[PDB]
Length: 269
Length: 268
Ligand SMILES: COCC(=O)N[C@@]1(C)CCS(=O)(=O)C1
Ligand SMILES: COCC(=O)N[C@@]1(C)CCS(=O)(=O)C1
Image (cartoon, rainbow over all chains, first blue to last red; front, top):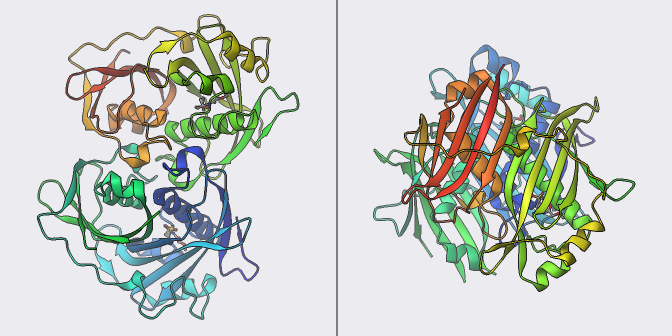
């Protein structure tokens, strides 16, 4: 992969692997989310971020700060087939003192048509205390060197799905998958649960009949608290709806502490 | 990925991804196992096997036959770092009427040095009845077209680890991880549990202390019975020792064996 000509965005191509695809022989939304995170890591490395797994700036290391995900939003028009080449372009934007945004466009390598788009919100956290904070002047200056200074949105529309408020599912849930736990393959190189794991866990409470007869079009996931290596998760889903819509809650199996909430939109094949 | 000059083996290069590595920023044995499976599928495709995810020959489709894994054996000398290029060469061989073997050699793309090797045994199964059988004359003839006819072994050494008989672990186990369940990411395109998942389940019952202070050098896994999508698995481990362990996966309810294996670990 490479920075584009102007050095303000990054492009990489991926061949879809045998083990990356579901029943339709097309890439899972989990495979898509891993590729988004891979190209994001390759971009961060190319613009001089830390290579220690935390992807920090100089100022962030000095102040013991990290980025954590607040939200991930993916819309897929066409899942790439097994052996297909997908091209993903990604860039970052500063959002004042609130946080930062990473955006992605997915294209068919052969046709050059857009097959999906994604957006993520990141907030600043002290690594030691785990307390959220605002972005410092010095960090905002670091982001000016490698981000477009005019707005560039994967989701430009002024009232678009990627920014909708998500309500909290009320008991009883319509469907549930209980006693979900992470294994070592679910952890990143710093022994935190991979953000993509939480996508899989949400989808586990979707009935197999939906997955068999629908394609996932849109997923919006809010991240509230991280699952520790030794935590156990319950995944809850209620139908809110030819298109199927669902409300999602992940919560700790014991005390019912919220870790994530989300929505999915599915269209019949 | 390409067939080599003689058309009797296949080579592919892989860049190690961010999410593929563990805590020393080198590829997990699970990442290695997924890459072995991927170059295996790419080779099968290049020599005219089915593209429906069952990777069958013409006479296998006629007879409703599939290959199932009996054994996977992997030895790693160096795990490739995050963003390193690993080159993997793979080939197949007939073992008379017993079954077939797929072998792999892993190389550092930059040095050309061997960083690991693996071998796997495959047995014929009727897809409908799930009954094991011998290889037909007609299937053995199909394998003559794309396999070396002289022996080529990733593990040549007569009486090597890759062919050792594995005993059944006796209760009580020294270590256990219980209530393991597959999710959709654990299934292949035909909704069978990915063979690599079973490797991860085996390793779940190794203490975090071992994984933190040792590197995995060798893993030998026998496959006895498939975990179904709605099954639950217990992973059991006992120290037999370098650290060496004996492994058992069994169904959480009735204790039906699904896999047994051994691991050998070297202090870092
Ligand atoms: C300036 O780049 C930082 C970055 O992208 N780092 C990530 C950890 C967040 C977005 S990610 O998940 O793609 C990888
Ligand atoms: C002609 O080769 C068939 C083949 O390789 N097929 C696999 C399914 C078994 C070995 S695998 O796991 O590498 C892929």
